[PDB]
Image: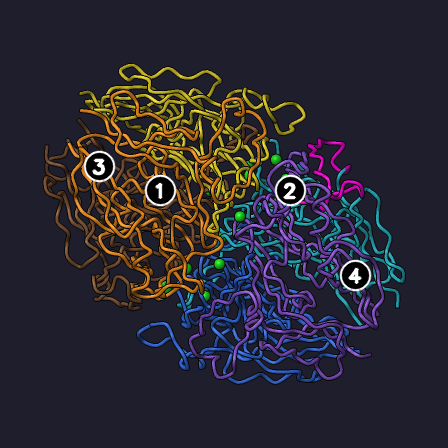
Chain colours: A blue, B cyan, C purple, D yellow, E orange, F brown
Amino acid sequence: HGFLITRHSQTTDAPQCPQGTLQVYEGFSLLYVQGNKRAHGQDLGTAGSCLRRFSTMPFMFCNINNVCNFASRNDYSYWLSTPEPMPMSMQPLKGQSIQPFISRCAVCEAPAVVIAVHSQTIQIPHCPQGWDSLWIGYSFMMHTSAGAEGSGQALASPGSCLEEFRSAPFIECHGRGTCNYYANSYSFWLATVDVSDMFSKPQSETLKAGDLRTRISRCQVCMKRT
Amino acid sequence: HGFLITRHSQTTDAPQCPQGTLQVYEGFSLLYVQGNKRAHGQDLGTAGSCLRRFSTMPFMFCNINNVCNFASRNDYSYWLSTPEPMPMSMQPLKGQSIQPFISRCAVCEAPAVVIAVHSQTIQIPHCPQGWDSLWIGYSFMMHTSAGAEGSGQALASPGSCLEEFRSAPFIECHGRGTCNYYANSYSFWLATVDVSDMFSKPQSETLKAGDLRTRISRCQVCMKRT
Amino acid sequence: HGFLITRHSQTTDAPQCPQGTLQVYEGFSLLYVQGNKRAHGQDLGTAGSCLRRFSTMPFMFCNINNVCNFASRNDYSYWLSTPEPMPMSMQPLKGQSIQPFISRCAVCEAPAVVIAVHSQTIQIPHCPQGWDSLWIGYSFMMHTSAGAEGSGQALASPGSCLEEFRSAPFIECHGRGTCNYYANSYSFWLATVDVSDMFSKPQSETLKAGDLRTRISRCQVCMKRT
Amino acid sequence: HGFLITRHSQTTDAPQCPQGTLQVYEGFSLLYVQGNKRAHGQDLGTAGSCLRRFSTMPFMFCNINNVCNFASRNDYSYWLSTPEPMPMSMQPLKGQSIQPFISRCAVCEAPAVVIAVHSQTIQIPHCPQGWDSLWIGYSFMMHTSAGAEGSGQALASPGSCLEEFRSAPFIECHGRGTCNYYANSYSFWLATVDVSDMFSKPQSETLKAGDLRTRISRCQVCMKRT
Amino acid sequence: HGFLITRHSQTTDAPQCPQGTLQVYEGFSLLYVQGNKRAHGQDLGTAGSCLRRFSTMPFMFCNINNVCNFASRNDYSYWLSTPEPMPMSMQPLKGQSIQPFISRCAVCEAPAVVIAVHSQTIQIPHCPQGWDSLWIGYSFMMHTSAGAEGSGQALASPGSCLEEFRSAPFIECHGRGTCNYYANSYSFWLATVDVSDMFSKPQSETLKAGDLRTRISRCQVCMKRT
Amino acid sequence: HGFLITRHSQTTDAPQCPQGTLQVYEGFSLLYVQGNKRAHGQDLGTAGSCLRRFSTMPFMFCNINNVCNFASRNDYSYWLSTPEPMPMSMQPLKGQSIQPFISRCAVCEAPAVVIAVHSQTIQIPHCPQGWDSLWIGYSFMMHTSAGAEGSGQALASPGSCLEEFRSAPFIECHGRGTCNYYANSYSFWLATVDVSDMFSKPQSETLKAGDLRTRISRCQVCMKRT
Ligand SMILES: [Cl-]
Ligand SMILES: [Cl-]
Ligand SMILES: [Cl-]
Ligand SMILES: [Cl-]
Ligand SMILES: [Cl-]
Ligand SMILES: [Cl-]
Ligand SMILES: [Cl-]
Ligand SMILES: [Cl-]
Ligand SMILES: [Cl-]
Ligand SMILES: [Cl-]
Ligand SMILES: [Cl-]
Ligand SMILES: [Cl-]
């Protein structure tokens, strides 16, 4: 049997397929699109989040009168990003200067089902008995950007287990050909919760650089041993 | 092979895994979350809807300047609920008084694929030939609450087949640590339709206590016999 | 093993299940529903997009006070449609005159996993090595209609691979019993991108009848050979 | 000089114009409309909230291809309502049975500017020096219903000063010709605040019948003496 | 005394101020803007709808970290338009080719208050006793476009009384410098209602070229005689 | 005659009423509220934006079953703010520590109509002939925060003319009793446009501290001389 998963490097290099899986293709890490203001995501654990080719506008829309428009309005695409910093000017990137910002991915064929498990603690959870580890990460749940629109990940999916934590894990691109980070680009992570605190008022916390991971749930991606 | 499913008790007791499946873990029935007003759900048939630990705030958000905030705004979580009535005062629940309201779940490993089928009638549908029954229920399609935001279930998924019908099957919780039912918490169910009525104007109906199930589609959850 | 997929005819005839799969049931092509303004879709590759019975109102909602309302507000359903033209008057369709407009579907059991692959070009992509073709099509990503609400397809799913391209692939139906096409019913397709253009400003294009497919990505639906 | 204001009876009888103003016309109390999901209100203090003629569908929409549609989709109108109770069945009202539910209004010409003032207490505020009282009421700020869409009042306007407090001050009507109250129809009132509490954590309260007004700000409508 | 009103030519020529008013300035007819997906309109009867200078991007946004961005995302402006047809290609307009599409306006000082009255019939309503006519028109209530966002007019305001009926009375412009009409650009007009029909099911109608005005309410703009 | 306007100090001191107007009352600068996710603003030029008393929760909501809830969900209020910096920790403010952050206002009675005029340049516009200056400022058009919801100002109103430019002119408060600035709190300002550039592609710009005002339109608030 064959089950297809995606791995995201969060760098300009394609990731290696995990041990016991084989590579199908490599591409660019698509997070979601926004057309006519409506966001639609592709689960990061699935082949849909790995497009063979990048574009700031990877879709087009058609109206009921048989007229289609490509990159001819104000639509968006969103992509997982690399550690590349914003330029000092903080101006949107255009053309070739976009490339260093876009995460790469690989689609891999697994011989069995692949899942994520989440600890809701700072400790990496163990795979269920009979399952083997593929990778470890941080519990990535949802995101919003323009218009507070966005999408999210299935916690059962490898897409909810991002290998590198980033406060700004994705970049916003436009039909007009620009990309940038924006002040309202938010990432939402499964949080830690202590057993004694489950029913208590959550203890509010604002975390700064160096402490961000103290409240982020950890995860492992696991494949059934057959 | 192994395929993971979730069963929800809709009570304060964890459900038993259905015959022919084995238990992986138990948890609390997460329906969806709402961050920066945007709702994101976890399919009730999948492990993502079963969190090991409850919290009124099971996530945190981070901004592009490497500052994260936990339970420090006005965000929500939503959980499948129990038969526990609202207090007479109808005041939000805090602390330990939340526990009796939260549904429990179990994640189970099945040896084969698990599906839901729906009748669009008051009769329970039969499993496809070659599939065996795991449980029966009511066709649960979507829900909305605060800001009319919400999420839904895949009808192909066991998550669309809720074992106990409830007009109010889920409770709303807040980062501030409260939970309650609200007047705008809506549940949407796959409805019945008679064959002769498929193309006709739907006959509008308002149903009261005792008659609610007369227009709710029934379902069965089925596992492929291998 | 068994994995369930859906095929949509986009005609008033049920489609035949592809070679190597067996029929489970036939129905009507449900795209999404909209209740209390919130859209919720059923992935076109899954059994949830194939309802045994059509209705302009295939759901009902319940409030927390144990009162349910069926077809008693202003809610919507959306269905894949046929080549049937709008009447000259462009008035909404009622009753039996709706039937010629609604696409049919079949749910088929496959012996192995079924995926879609997308080329991002005008050429049909090839199935991965070890996978066999079930059908070819056009990369269908998302849609919006009333209130710019909508839903979309998973690119990994057969639901993202529509066999016939249509500018207007779906019709809007109402609880009141009417259906029609509307000026704001938009379809969004995965677009073509040339390798040399990936980082460049997308070349904006408005396409008219005869040229629409020049910028639509192609796809194939593939089943793992076991 | 002449300045036009509206008074709303919240009954099936037109209100009398206040002392020192003269009647222009009488009508029906329009609160807001909702077209293509988007709400648009008419300030209750202005002539726009007083339509000469009632209809469940008082508007029509046109598309860019010179086709207009009247009462041919799923649009709404909202009207201030009377003390008429919901029928026991809680079914939507149709036809002549709608009339007892709709508030009446009168548009009056004032010789000078007319304002509202608000106390943020259970005591009626006094008119500014040089202004005379026209009526007293309760501070009505905003409302939501279908899709959590809605509109509100300007606190400087007489429209923010509703003469009779009602938990359910408005009814929802549809293009299809029905009206009803719905569980998600919310009214928002300017609340009371004690001076010592301005910076403190607000003391959360759930109020039941008999106590609702204990936290509602009071208002007066005032006309400049010339 | 002085009260400022706006008149819109719906042509490339500035309108003349009505008899008994004097010109303050001339400009371009701004309908609304859309920033971070949120629409905000300027009442067409007020000076805010008459900008001295046109731009496809007449605003800029700032974030809390003292960084402002001008025309550097995917934001919109909307302007009342002229009778200029779409080019045959239906491609967005850029640069100088935008000018023929943009309506002009004049801001005029009136010696007294200026109102609109609406008939809800195909007959022009009369001004209230003591008020004189400035112009006649059609009852323009609201509009939506991208993301079904939009804004509307106050029926008490001259802005709700558009002198020329147009199915497509406004054009959409973008920060990137393009303008076009789009399939989802909707105009909403106060409709006609017969007295005998007020409580009846509205008679649904689809109107084509030549018949559009048969269901549009008429209006007059009136100034108090002092 | 009397016309009421509001002036906002953007400091912890009440502003003085401008020359030729007299004080009615002083209060706190309310920008908008957000209930059940829906934003509703009070025009900054009007008395509604000046509340006698501050509260993080200045409203309450009621449901159709005669139950009202005050500060018992996840609702917001937004207030114009002072130059007070965020604490270093960037944690939300509670209790008395909120006071230094909240702008004060005064409501003033003018003997004639008060307007704003806007230059769309870095130069302050002149009052129309026959009008006298009350104050000068910067053209403040709209704002968004939580859920990208927000409201805006009428450009004809003094509320669109803010006396001190601030990148972060408003603070977000919650029913739970906290206030803070958030990464997605955006302010939108009327921008400058050169005459030669009106029809050209807008020249995109990202401005940093020291240069922000280079693209902000200026305004004056003017009162008719009687
Ligand atoms: Cl675009
Ligand atoms: Cl930004
Ligand atoms: Cl929170
Ligand atoms: Cl409630
Ligand atoms: Cl309905
Ligand atoms: Cl239409
Ligand atoms: Cl309608
Ligand atoms: Cl209801
Ligand atoms: Cl822009
Ligand atoms: Cl279009
Ligand atoms: Cl609250
Ligand atoms: Cl933040």
Task: List the residue tagged with mark 1.
Answer: E164
Can residue D197 be seen here? The reply is: no
SS at badge 3: loop
Label 2 close to label 1 by CB (< 8 Å): no
**Dot 1 lies on which element?**
loop
Task: State if disc 3 and disc 4 touch (CB < 8 Å).
Answer: no
Q: Chain of mark 1?
A: E
Identify the mark at residue E18; answer none if there is no mark. 3
Q: Earlier in the sequence, mark 3 or mark 1?
A: 3
Going by the numbered disc 1, the residue's amino acid type is Glu
Which subunit holds the residue at mark 4? Answer: C
Tell me the crowding category of disc 1: few under 14, some 14 to 19, or many 20 or more residues within 10 angstroms, Cα based: some
Q: Position of residue D34 (x, y in %)?
A: 49, 40
Segment colored magenta = B187-214
Q: Secondary structure at mark 2?
A: strand
Depth-wise, is mark 2 or mark 1 nearer the camera? 1
Q: Which residue is mark 2?
A: C178
Image mark 2: chain: C
